[PDB]
Image (cartoon, coloured by chain):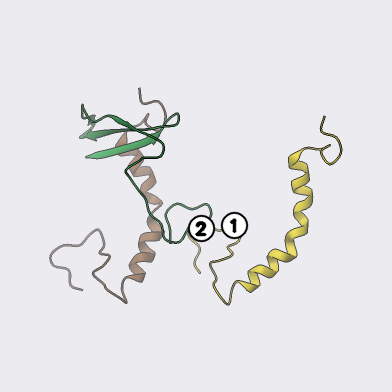
Chain colours: A brown, B yellow, C green
Amino acid sequence: EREGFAAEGAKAVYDRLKNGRQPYETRAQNCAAVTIPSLFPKESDNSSTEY
Amino acid sequence: EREGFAAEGAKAVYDRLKNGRQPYETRAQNCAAVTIPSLFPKESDNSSTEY
Amino acid sequence: VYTHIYRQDDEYLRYEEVEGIEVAGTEGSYPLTACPYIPVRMVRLDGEDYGR
């Protein structure tokens, strides 16, 4: 009955581990700004963003 | 029962002989900093370090 | 919708969850060498998740 690794649910494991990706996204955003700015967009972009 | 060369366990030998490798590591780090600085990382590095 | 895959006793298990409950009919099991999810890295270091 969901003993190990699954005793708390799916939306709970996803929120604890979400803070480990922080350096990689920042470093990729720094890389993808002198070659193609539209290759790696942020997570807060919409129709009005200009590259 | 594990006679000579084996009279103090596996962990005791490792920590005693660990001290002989220091010059080689110190020299390898100097060598691997003008060619490619991410080929010989130290033993105390993590996701935040920058090369 | 969320999907969860975890290791238990030399195999893999899965299920699917919506809202806050579990959708019936989505359970399953995969072998230890035929998981159809493939994380890929380019440059691999020692002791880190993900890749450079």
Q: Tag 2, which chain?
A: C
Q: Helix, strand or loop at disc 2?
A: loop
Please name the residue that numbered disc 2 is placed on: C45
Vertical placement of residue C3 versus B1, above or below: below
Q: Tag 1, which chain?
A: B
Between A30 and C4, which is closer to the camera in this rendering?
A: C4
Q: Helix, strand or loop at disc 1?
A: loop
Write the residue at 59% across / 65% down. B40
How far separated are the C-alphas under marks 1 and 2? 13 Å
Q: Position of residue A2 (x, y in %)?
A: 36, 26
Q: In this image, B38 relative to A47: left or right?
A: right
Please name the residue that numbered disc 1 is placed on: B44
Dots 1 and 2 on the same chain: no
Q: In this image, B44 relative to A29: left or right?
A: right
Residue type of the residue flagged with mark 2: Leu
Judge the density around disc 2: few (<14), some (14-19), many (≥20) Cα neighbours within 10 Å.
Answer: some
Q: Are marks 1 and 2 in contact (CB under 8 Å)?
A: no
Q: Position of residue B3 (x, y in %)?
A: 85, 35
Q: Quadrant of residue A12?
A: top left
